[PDB]
Image (tube, rainbow over all chains, first blue to last red):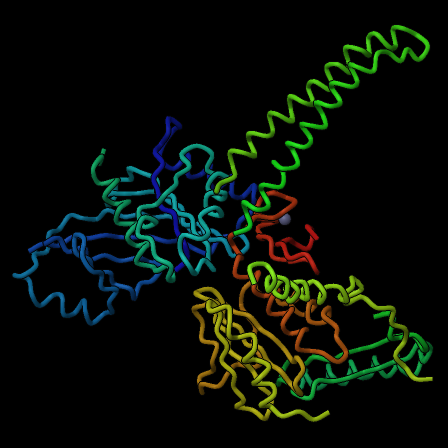
Length: 193
Length: 55
Length: 267
Ligand SMILES: [Zn+2]
């Protein structure tokens, strides 16, 4: 929907995973941003062809079903009912609970989803996500998001997202941000630790 | 009821303005098309002789 | 082509300036001396002017070749009746004058009906260019025309007229139902966005700014020309404060007669 930037920043030699998260939240409170609640993105893989059957708490009705690289079905509940019936064409492939859990913040129609990355129970990362509401068209407001990133991150300021290479002049889609989230999951699942 | 009463109260204020103050001139005009809750009205307090300059 | 025919002007002036300047170099050194009281005010000025005129010749020579680099490259009786029509175009500009729009109006106090097809002919004149925007004229309620305008992939605007004059204008984004559930155009609502509600006030101030007592066509044309600058929104930083966000707000306010994005604090 709105243009989103997704990245990781590590512990960065300060205490623990959540210490830098609390530093970012107290920086945002110095700016003075109000909250809108929490958020969590959960993933789960399937295979016979890797099926990413995956969910987000921002849109719980949106059940994302992706290939490894093909089309994405942002489908409803009855698709999840149909998905159970195969069980031989597409095996369960359990133990894929790579999730991002955190809170959302608002500052004058600006939204931030900030939290930590866990492999189920054990947290081994920090997810950083910035976004803006009325960003309809993509690749036209990246100066705004870059300014917002350098405003309060300081170190570990990211840039040039992977879906920005998917250049098109239409409306930015939630699939782009979602793609960014699964690329984030691919970035974090390699190190484990 | 609150919309009607608030329009009546605004009318009372502008009638107090008209009766109390006739010095420059008073003009009140209303939109011919209106909503159930919100309205849009035009209030003009402009001098007696040279209104076409002070725009 | 005229780019070379006007770039040749600097060189054809520069060579004659070279001739004049070398003539000055000759005769000023040939003039002898003008002491003007003290000698130190002359003999120290001797080397000053001798450097001055020689360096003027040198800089004229030097700026000759940068102009030379950029440049590139019945018999005569009926030719006379050709260019007079072309100078009649200048004759059209002879009686123009710079007085233009500005007048010396006093108070207008002493001591109508037009068809909607005329409004359609008005709206057909300016919709023919700017293909990135669209106009959809409709009158589902009376003879008054309210119009749907889409702006590329950015904005959806409802523009209500009445009595051939301006009634109202409300702007929203690109991913909202500007119609109602019945399908008619929405009349009374809100844009549900802080920036959009903030700039609707600027639109209301702008419609009361363009004031023509007889000629509302140029009023609405200047209005839509002003609106055309708003397809650059969220893409151009502010002209005085550098950054986009002033208290989180990008520059939006285009000044009257000088269209550039500002804020209320940024004026
Ligand atoms: Zn500014």
